Length: 363
Ligand SMILES: Cc1ccc(F)cc1CCCCOc1ccc(C(=O)Nc2cccc3c2O[C@H](C(=O)O)CN3CCCC(=O)O)cc1
Ligand SMILES: CC(C)CCC[C@@H](C)[C@H]1CC[C@H]2[C@@H]3CC=C4C[C@@H](O)CC[C@]4(C)[C@H]3CC[C@]12C
Ligand SMILES: CCCCCCCC/C=C\CCCCCCCC(=O)O
Ligand SMILES: CCCCCCCC/C=C\CCCCCCCC(=O)O
Image (cartoon, rainbow, N blue to C red; front, side):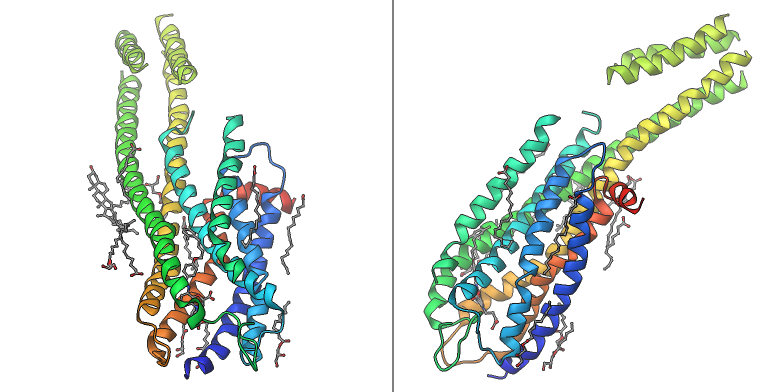
């Protein structure tokens, strides 16, 4: 079949591109992660696990490239071929779950921007669960260099066809479609919460500026406005935040009841309210960026690959090439592999003190 001629040129190129790009990206990302910083978070745990998985997988790519560069002749021994298969699939599904967990965590965080020792350890416990389950689910590959007159690895063949037809069925459903479903619900929930919270924040800021413009324009009415604002704040009852705001109000109302000092003190509420707003806004930015990048990764790297893989398995026959479908599969397999060098975009644009650690390293 002519696809083999296509493969022997196509795979070395993309595998080595992914190798070098991924070594640079992941090596630098892991170096940054491990830099000391005053605070740490569970999302750093999940990102670190993802980057380690990707770099381990990337370390296998020069061997696959060698395979194809030798005319599809494997020289590295039977165990190494087994490990090629195992590393490919363990990386793929560990990555999918680490991404899904990361999106879920960002949602749960944006719900509660203000309010633990335990969640750092919990992130490791969860990661360990994911590793155990995926590694145990994949050990089939370790139990199954086959060919004669040449040594062939990485190839679909009759011996394994039925096996993979069954295995696909589970990995398609639990390893791909269920996580993408979880992501789609997460997207819906992120958008809903973000829109509602920012509408509320705009209302809050607008009423504050109205009251402050009233105080700026017109001492008899200053006390009235301050008492109305104090009553509104008490009915709003972040105990320390409310107490700080109320203490601002009480200081202004004292400086009034004692016109220059009180009107000036009125402005101090504005900067504290802007910081209160910014905390929420940062949490929402992070969640939305994460979910968008992750959905794009899924559309590019994983769903086309699983679709074409499934159809390739279902229609496979011993003496037929199907070069066009097979070529499409080869390309989407490349994309799935390339996820391992794509993921540091997420570390850079949605990291947790990532740029802070990076600036520290630069110092
Ligand atoms: C079970 C489970 C559920 C949820 C999870 F999160 C995790 C798991 C554990 C997953 C364990 C692994 O599961 C699998 C593994 C493989 C599969 C599967 O279809 N394989 C498959 C399908 C079609 C072609 C090939 C194929 O693989 C061949 C090869 O590797 O040798 C090479 N080629 C040839 C590629 C083209 C070329 O180069 O000519 C399908 C499933
Ligand atoms: C992963 C892809 C397919 C997601 C696209 C799904 C579409 C249909 C989603 C994305 C954003 C979602 C919307 C987000 C916010 C709201 C406001 C809520 O009060 C009613 C539902 C509504 C209007 C959702 C409807 C469904 C929705 C429009
Ligand atoms: C990804 C390519 C193939 C790799 C096979 C599996 C390799 C596992 C390597 C690193 C996983 C690190 C495990 C740390 C999580 C355990 C944490 C804990 O138990 O508290
Ligand atoms: C992969 C994404 C699929 C596309 C889904 C399309 C639905 C988009 C709908 C709403 C997105 C709203 C973006 C946020 C606007 C914020 C403006 C504001 O809050 O003031």
